[PDB]
Length: 345
Image 1 (tube, rainbow, N blue to C red):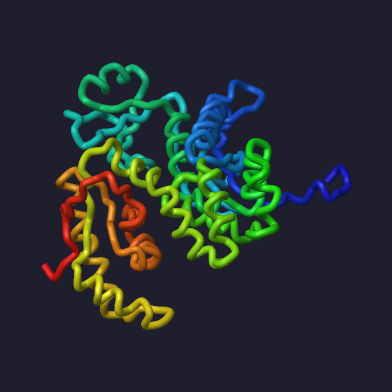
Image 2 (cartoon, rainbow, N blue to C red):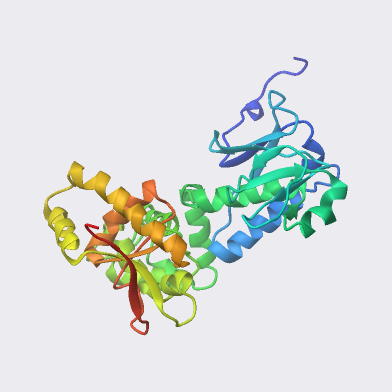
């Protein structure tokens, strides 16, 4: 090379990044328009004012070993999603109800997982009236990105993001903060709690309710896996109204009164569960889920309080569509009806 090297030649890994084929560089060009960059901002905005923290920047760059109209979405250096995005064209998607067909590359939407087909421009107004849904090129990339963050929000919420939130809270209710961390709770413990809250789709905007609940229970309990379940009940009204809006009936999944005992036997049994029970659970749990998908009911499981923190820890790694709540996280002012049962069939 022409110029000598300096430590600025060291490329530290990026929390969130994107690699882009040379056909997309125009839509990701700082210098030119930047059609996509405007959408990544309004995603990262509508994520702070929604999920309660600021997603890390999306470091975008070109990698010419990629197909010209293909992108990789990266997390801490490793791929978490790829896709194609042809510029001048448009994407049309069937929400399962459209009528007809169109000429173009048949494909699958990276977001909802739906069947879709890229189309040309002038089919725009014609594709919609056939029942389709049409979004621009750059918008596909964005919707694929806004979907990869809400799925990986737990891992994007690093220790740096927790202090930056501890600092943001501490400029509006600083008294809660001045003597909580590192005083009563260590930042190691705060982050892991907020991280567990995120990993189960529970938002952390109510840092008042959280930093209050912590400083109350923190001295006589320092296990974040137990502090968490305490903070969940303080957010019981927010977790409730998140999946069961209004004050109408609560359509829940339920487990057997004795299977509970079967499961409750396994709790104090030690630090683990026994094999044969597992493969049965996943099957019947997905059985109950399937009935819900046809009743129009949410995929919410409702269990004994001491049965949540491991059913979630177990069932969610296989069916991350599922929600595992407790009877202490639901408000007292709601009627409950077990729309489906995990039983011996």
